[PDB]
Amino acid sequence: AQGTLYIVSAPSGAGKSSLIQALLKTQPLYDTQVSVSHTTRQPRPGEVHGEHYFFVNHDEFKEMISRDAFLEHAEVFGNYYGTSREAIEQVLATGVDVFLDIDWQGAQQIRQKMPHARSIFILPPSKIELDRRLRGRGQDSEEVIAKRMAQAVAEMSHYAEYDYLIVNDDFDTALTDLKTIIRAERLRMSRQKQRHDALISKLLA
Amino acid sequence: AQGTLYIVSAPSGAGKSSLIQALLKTQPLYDTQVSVSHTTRQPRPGEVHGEHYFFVNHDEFKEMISRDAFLEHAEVFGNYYGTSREAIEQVLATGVDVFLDIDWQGAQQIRQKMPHARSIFILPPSKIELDRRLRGRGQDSEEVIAKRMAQAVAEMSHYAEYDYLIVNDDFDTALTDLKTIIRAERLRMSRQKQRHDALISKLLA
Amino acid sequence: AQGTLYIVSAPSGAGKSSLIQALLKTQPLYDTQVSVSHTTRQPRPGEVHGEHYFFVNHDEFKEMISRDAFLEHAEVFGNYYGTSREAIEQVLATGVDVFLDIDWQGAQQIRQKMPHARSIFILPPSKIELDRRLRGRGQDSEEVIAKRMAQAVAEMSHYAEYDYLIVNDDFDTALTDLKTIIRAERLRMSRQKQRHDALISKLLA
Amino acid sequence: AQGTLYIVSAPSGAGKSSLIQALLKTQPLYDTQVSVSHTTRQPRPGEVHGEHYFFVNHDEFKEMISRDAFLEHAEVFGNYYGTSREAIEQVLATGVDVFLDIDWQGAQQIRQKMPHARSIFILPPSKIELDRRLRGRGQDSEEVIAKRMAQAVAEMSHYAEYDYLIVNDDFDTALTDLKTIIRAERLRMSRQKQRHDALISKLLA
Amino acid sequence: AQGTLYIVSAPSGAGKSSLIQALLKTQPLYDTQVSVSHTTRQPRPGEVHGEHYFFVNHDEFKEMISRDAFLEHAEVFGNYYGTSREAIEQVLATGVDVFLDIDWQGAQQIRQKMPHARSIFILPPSKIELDRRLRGRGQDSEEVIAKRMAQAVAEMSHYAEYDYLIVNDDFDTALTDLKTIIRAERLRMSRQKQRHDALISKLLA
Amino acid sequence: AQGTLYIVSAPSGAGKSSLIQALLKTQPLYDTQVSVSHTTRQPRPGEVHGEHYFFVNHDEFKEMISRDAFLEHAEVFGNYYGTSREAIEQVLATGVDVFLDIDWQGAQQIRQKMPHARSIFILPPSKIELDRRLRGRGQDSEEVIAKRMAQAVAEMSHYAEYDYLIVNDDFDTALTDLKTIIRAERLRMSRQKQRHDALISKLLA
Ligand SMILES: Nc1nc2c(ncn2[C@@H]2O[C@H](COP(=O)(O)OP(=O)(O)O)[C@@H](O)[C@H]2O)c(=O)[nH]1
Ligand SMILES: Nc1nc2c(ncn2[C@@H]2O[C@H](COP(=O)(O)OP(=O)(O)O)[C@@H](O)[C@H]2O)c(=O)[nH]1
Ligand SMILES: Nc1nc2c(ncn2[C@@H]2O[C@H](COP(=O)(O)OP(=O)(O)O)[C@@H](O)[C@H]2O)c(=O)[nH]1
Ligand SMILES: Nc1nc2c(ncn2[C@@H]2O[C@H](COP(=O)(O)OP(=O)(O)O)[C@@H](O)[C@H]2O)c(=O)[nH]1
Ligand SMILES: Nc1nc2c(ncn2[C@@H]2O[C@H](COP(=O)(O)OP(=O)(O)O)[C@@H](O)[C@H]2O)c(=O)[nH]1
Ligand SMILES: Nc1nc2c(ncn2[C@@H]2O[C@H](COP(=O)(O)OP(=O)(O)O)[C@@H](O)[C@H]2O)c(=O)[nH]1
Ligand SMILES: Nc1nc2c(ncn2[C@@H]2O[C@H](CO)[C@@H](O)[C@H]2O)c(=O)[nH]1
Ligand SMILES: Nc1nc2c(ncn2[C@@H]2O[C@H](CO)[C@@H](O)[C@H]2O)c(=O)[nH]1
Ligand SMILES: Nc1nc2c(ncn2[C@@H]2O[C@H](CO)[C@@H](O)[C@H]2O)c(=O)[nH]1
Ligand SMILES: Nc1nc2c(ncn2[C@@H]2O[C@H](CO)[C@@H](O)[C@H]2O)c(=O)[nH]1
Ligand SMILES: Nc1nc2c(ncn2[C@@H]2O[C@H](CO)[C@@H](O)[C@H]2O)c(=O)[nH]1
Ligand SMILES: Nc1nc2c(ncn2[C@@H]2O[C@H](CO)[C@@H](O)[C@H]2O)c(=O)[nH]1
Ligand SMILES: [K+]
Ligand SMILES: [K+]
Ligand SMILES: [K+]
Ligand SMILES: [K+]
Ligand SMILES: [K+]
Ligand SMILES: [K+]
C-alpha cells in the first residue's frame, strides 16, 4: 500500500510554511507527515535538529551527494537543501502521504523519479500583498527587499509546472483548499479500491 | 472557457439522488448545474416537465435517436433515458460544470465522446444497509425487492471504471466528499491559470 | 434492527418547528423522519394533507380513539391531536429514527408505552425573548397574546420530565445541538455493535 | 457541581492518543482536562514528568498501592499504570469533566467506584489498517508485530463493556464523533438543570 | 427594542439575489426578514404576490408616491420600485433585522431618513466573470447583453458609499461573509447590553 | 496600509487568555499578532521572556515610564504592566492587526491615542460560573476567593466602554464570535477599498 508524495512550492511571502504546519496539526502520523530535509544553512532561533531540518556542514552535504544519498538536492539563495531517499521510501511504503516543502528545482527532480507525486503551488493574492508579506516586521533596507522580491519573481515563473494552484489571499480559505486537495486525491478510485478492499467484495457478493 | 463534465452513477439505495440535489442548493447556476435528461418513464407526483426530466413518449424518443440528438442513450429499469447533446455543449461553453446523473451504459458512451469527463461512482456502506434502503418503507413484496437488489448488484459491478469512489455511509460526509471533488478539480492548474490570468501576469512583472 | 423514537416538546416561541424541518433537510428518509400526526385543526395556507398532518373532522378523530388507533392522543390549544400507532411501528422497524413533535401530555403516554423513547425539551433564552417571539408581527391583541403566554408557561412547567434540554437562543447553535444529540445516540454501543457487526467479527480474529 | 469522568480505551493503532490531544486543544481547563497517570515505564523522548505521566520506580508504585493511593491501577504490557484518587476527586469537584486514557482493566475498576462515568471505545476501521498503523515506521521484526497485534486483539475483545463506540477510519470524522459525545452529554437534563439554574426559574416565573 | 436595517446593493451578475435567499433559510422570522418591495414589473414564472414583491400597476404606484407611502422609491431597469414605510417600521419595532434589497438610488434616500441603517455592497471577482454571469445561458443577443453590462458598470460606480464590501467570487465564502457581518453587528455593545440585561445586573452585584 | 488595533479585556475567569491564544493559532503573523507587554510580576512556570512578557524589575519599569516608552501603562493587582509604543507602531505600519490583552485602565489610554482601535469585552455567563472558573483547582481559602471576585466585579463595571461584548458561555461559540468580529471588520469599506485596490479599478473600467 504505497502512499502519495505531495510537492508544495511557493515564493517566500505566499505563507507556505504556515499552511503546511496547520494542515499537519489536523492529521495523525499514520496518514500524513512532512519530510525533514538536509540543509547547510544556520538553524534559526527555535529550530531543533531533526524536526525542521538535519543541519550539516558544507563538506558533509558534499559527502552525501557523492554517495547518492538524495532523491533531490539543489542550491537555494546561498545554501544547499535536499531530501534523503532512505527516509522517504521507508515512510511511503507504510502508506503515509508525505509533504515535501521544496523549491521548483527539487520539484522537477522529484517529478521524474516519482511520476505519481502531486504538486501544489501557492501564490500570494497580489504583488502589493506579496511585497508586504516579504517585508516582514519592516526593518530591512529597500535594497535587501528588491533582492527578495526578485528571488520571489523567479520562483513564481515556474508555477505552471504544478498540478494545483492555491491563491493564498485568506489563510482559512487556503488551508481548506489544501485539505480539499488531499481529501479529493484520497477519493480516487485506485486509493479507494484498496482501503476499501472489499466491503466491495461483499457488495458484488 | 470550458466547464467540466461530471458523471455520477450508483445503484439505487446509494442516496445518489438526494446527494446531487443537496449539492445544487449550495451552488449558483453560473457555477454548477444538472443536465435535464429525456425519458419515457412517467412523471412522479410533484415532478415538473423540463426541470428534472423532459418526459416523452416511446415514439418521440425513438425519433430522437434517429436525428442523432443524444450524446448518450440507454435502456434503464424498463424505460429509455438519453442526454441531449445541444444543451450540454451550450452550458459547458458558458463555464458551468455540468452533472450527468446517468447509468454505467451511459457513462461509457460519454467517456468515448468526451474523454476529459470526470466520473464519480457512489456505493452503499454494506449489503445489509443497501437492502435496508432499497426496502424503503417496507411495503413492497419480496419479489419486487428481489428484482431491485439484482439490478443494484449489476450496477455495482461496473464501479472500477470510474475516476472517483464515494462510500455513502453518512450523508453529510458523502455530501462533503462530493463538494470536495468538485472543489479540488477547480484548483487544478489548467482552470486556475484561466481564472487568475490577470493576477498571474501582474505577479510575473 | 430498530430505529430510536425521539420526543420533542416546547412551548410555542421556542422555534421548535423550524428546528425540526431544518434538521430533516440534512437527513435521508432512510435515516430520519417526522411522524405524521392526525388532528382536527384546519390546514394552514400552503399545507398539504398527509405530509405535515392527517387532517380529520371531530367525529372521525373520536372514532379513531375508539378503534385504539393512537399510541398517544391529547387535547392541545383547542384541538385534538394524535399519533397513529401503525406508521410509527412500521417506520421504526426499518431502522429509521422517528421524531414525534408532540406536547407534554403526549410525551407522558409515549414514555409509558415506549420506555426507550428519548425526549428533547426546548426552551427560549429568556421570558422577554419568549414574549418577543410569541408577539410575532405584533398585530394580535393584548388579550390573545395573554392566552398564548399562559399556555407557554404551562408547557414549560413540564420540562424536568425530559432527557435532554436545548436552550434555543441562537438558531444555528440549537440546530447543532439537535443534530448532536441524534449523532451521539447513534454512537451508543447497542447501535454501533449492530451497524459494524461485520467489522467487529473480523477484528476479533 | 460535580463533573463527569470519561473513560477512553482502545488497542494501540486505533489513534486514541492523537484523538484526545486534539480534543483537549479545543477546550479550556475549566471545562475539560486529562488525568495524569502514574507509571513505572521509561519516559520516551519528548515526554516530561507531570505532563503526560508521573514516572516512578517499581518500588514507589508498590508503596502507592499499599497506602490506597489509586482509584484504579493495573499492569499493561510489562509495566504498571494507575490513576491517583486525590487529584481526580479534586478536579471533578470543581465541575471539570476529566478524560482517563486507560486500558480495559482500569475502566472496570473505575465503573464500579464511579457509576456515572461514561466510557468510549475506539476501533480501527479494519485489521489491515490496524496492522499498518501498528507497524509504524516499519522497522520492527515480523515477530514483534505479531505480538503487538495479539495484544491489540486482547484489548478489542473488551469493547462491548463501553457505552460508546467510535470507528476511527477518518481522523476528522472520529474527532467530531468525540466532541459530539461530550457535547450531547452536556445537553442532558441533569447537567442543564444546573448550569442553567434559572433562566428557567425566570421562565416558569 | 429595535432591530437593525440593512441595505444590500449590487450590479446584476454579483449573485446578490441567491445570497439573500440562502441567508434567510438559516434564520428565523423573529431574527431576520427581507422587506417586500412594491413594483410595476411583471411577476416571474413561479413568483407569488406579497412574498417576493407586491406587484402593482403603473397607475397604482404613482398614487402610492402621492400618499407618501414610500421610505424610498426609484426607477430601476425600466420599472418602478419602492419600499413601503409602514411594514419596515413595524418589523423593526419587534426586534427583527430587516434587509432591503434595493439599488443605489434607494440606498441614498434610506441613508438620509434612517442614518443608523447599515449598507452592504456586493462585487463580482472580475469583469470577465461579471460578463460570464450576465451572459447567463448565452441565448441573449449581443445588444441586450451590451445594455445589461452598462447598467452593471453604472451600478458599481456607487460602491464607495456603502459601509461594507463583499467580493462574491466563491458563493459559500460570500455567504459566510454576509452571515459574518450580521453576527458581528449583533455583538456590538448597544445590542448585547440589551439582550443580556439580566445577566449584566447580576454580575455587577 | 495601517493595521487595526484590537483591545481585549475581561475579569479573570471569563477565559480571555485561552480565547486569544486559540484565535492566534489560526492566523499567520502577517495578518494578526499579539503584543508583548512589559510587567514587573514574576514569570510563572512555563513562561518565557519575550513571548508572553518582557519581565522587568520595579526600577526598570520606572525608567521606561520616565522616558515615555509606553503607549499605555497601569498598575493591576500589585504589579505594573504596559505596552511599549515602538514595537506597536512598527508592527501596525506593516498592515498587521494587533491584539492588546490589557485591563480597562490600559484600554482607556489606548482609546484616546488611537481612536480607530476596536475594543472587545468578555463576560462569563453568570456569577456562579464566574466563581467556579475563579476558584480554579479549588485549593485557595474562601478569603482569597472573595478578594478575587471583588477584583473581577471591579473589572466588569467598565464593560460598557467597549465596542463589542462576548458572553463566553461556551468556548467554541465565543471563539467563533471573536473570529467573526475580526472578519467583519475586514469587510469594512475602508479596509476593502485598499487590499482590493482595483479589481475595482478594473471593474469600473
Ligand atoms: N530543492 C529543495 N528545496 C528546499 C528543500 N528544503 C527547503 N527548500 C526550499 O528552500 C526555500 C527556503 O527555505 P527556508 O530557509 O526554510 O525559508 P522558508 O521556508 O521560506 O521560511 C524554500 O523555497 C524551500 O522550498 C529541499 O529539501 N529541497
Ligand atoms: N444513461 C442514461 N441513464 C440515465 C439518464 N437519466 C437517468 N438515468 C439513469 O436511470 C436511472 C433513473 O432512475 P430514476 O427514474 O430517475 O429514479 P432514481 O434512481 O431515484 O433517479 C438512474 O440510474 C439514472 O442514472 C440518462 O439521461 N441516460
Ligand atoms: N400530544 C400530541 N400533541 C401534538 C401532536 N401533534 C402536534 N402536537 C402538539 O400540539 C401543538 C401543535 O401546534 P401546531 O398547530 O402544529 O402549531 P405549532 O406549535 O407551530 O406546531 C404543539 O405543541 C405540538 O406539540 C400529536 O400528535 N399528539
Ligand atoms: N489501567 C490503566 N491503564 C493505563 C493508564 N495509563 C495508560 N494506560 C494504558 O496503557 C496503555 C499503553 O500506554 P502508553 O505507554 O502510553 O502507549 P500508548 O498510549 O498507546 O501510546 C494504553 O492502553 C493505556 O490505556 C492508567 O492510568 N491506568
Ligand atoms: N430603490 C429600489 N430598488 C429596488 C427595490 N426593489 C428592488 N430594487 C432594485 O431593482 C433591481 C431589481 O431587479 P429584479 O427585478 O428584482 O431582478 P434581480 O436583480 O435579480 O433582483 C435590483 O437592483 C434591486 O436592487 C426597491 O424597493 N427600491
Ligand atoms: N494596562 C495593561 N494591562 C495589562 C497589560 N498586560 C496584562 N494586563 C492585564 O493584567 C491582568 C492580569 O494579567 P496576568 O498576570 O497575565 O493574568 P491573566 O491574564 O488573567 O491570566 C489582565 O487583566 C490583563 O488585562 C498591559 O500591557 N497593560
Ligand atoms: N507584514 C508583516 N509580515 C510579517 C510580520 N512578521 C512576520 N511576517 C511575515 O509572516 C511570514 C512568516 O510566516 C513571512 O512572510 C513574514 O515576512 C510582520 O510584522 N508584518
Ligand atoms: N429504511 C427506510 N428507507 C426509506 C423509507 N422511506 C424511504 N426510504 C428510502 O430512502 C431513499 C429515498 O430518499 C430510498 O432509498 C428509499 O427506499 C423508510 O421509511 N425507511
Ligand atoms: N419578532 C417577530 N417575530 C416574528 C415575526 N414574524 C414571525 N415571527 C415569529 O417567528 C416564529 C415563526 O417562525 C414565531 O414564533 C412567530 O411569532 C416578526 O415580524 N417579528
Ligand atoms: N503507517 C505508519 N504509521 C505510523 C508512522 N509513524 C507513526 N505511525 C503510527 O501513528 C500512531 C502514533 O500516533 C501509531 O499508531 C504509530 O504506529 C509511519 O511512518 N507509518
Ligand atoms: N454562465 C452561466 N450563467 C448562468 C446560467 N444560467 C443562469 N446563469 C446565471 O446565474 C445567475 C442566476 O442564478 C445569473 O447571473 C444568470 O445569468 C448558465 O447556464 N451559465
Ligand atoms: N473549575 C476549574 N477551573 C480551572 C481549573 N484549572 C484551571 N481553571 C481555570 O481555567 C482558567 C485558566 O485558563 C482560569 O479561569 C482557571 O481558574 C480546574 O481544575 N477547575
Ligand atoms: K523542507
Ligand atoms: K438524469
Ligand atoms: K406532530
Ligand atoms: K493515561
Ligand atoms: K426588494
Ligand atoms: K498583555
Image (spheres, coloured by chain):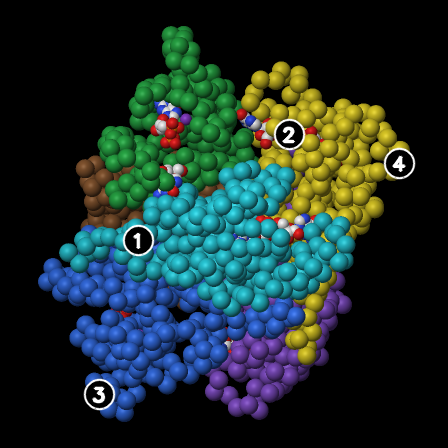
Chain colours: A yellow, B purple, C blue, D cyan, E brown, F green
For residue C169, the mark is: 1
**Is residue C37 in view?**
no
Q: Disc 4 marks which amino acid?
A: Arg
Q: Disc 2 marks which amino acid?
A: Glu
Image height of E40 relative to D42, above or below = below
The residue singled out by tag 2 in the image is A47
Chain assignment, label 2 = A
Cα distance in 3D space between marks 1 and 4: 67 Å
Q: Disc 3 marks which amino acid?
A: Lys
Residue A129 lies in what quarter of the image?
top right
Whether the residues at callouts 2 and 3 have beta carbons within 8 Å, the answer is: no
Residue F148 lies in what quarter of the image?
top left
Cα distance in 3D space between marks 1 and 2: 47 Å
Residue located at (46% from left, 65% from top): D163
Q: Quadrant of the C terminus of chain D?
A: bottom left
Q: Disc 1 marks which amino acid?
A: Asp
The residue singled out by tag 3 in the image is C62
- Disc nearer the start of the sequence (4/2): 2
Foreground disc of the pair 3, 4: 4
Residue B110 lies in what quarter of the image?
bottom right
The residue closer to the viewer here, C49 or D122, is D122
- Percent from the top left, x then y, of residue B160? 72, 69
- Percent from the top left, x then y, of residue D109? 46, 59
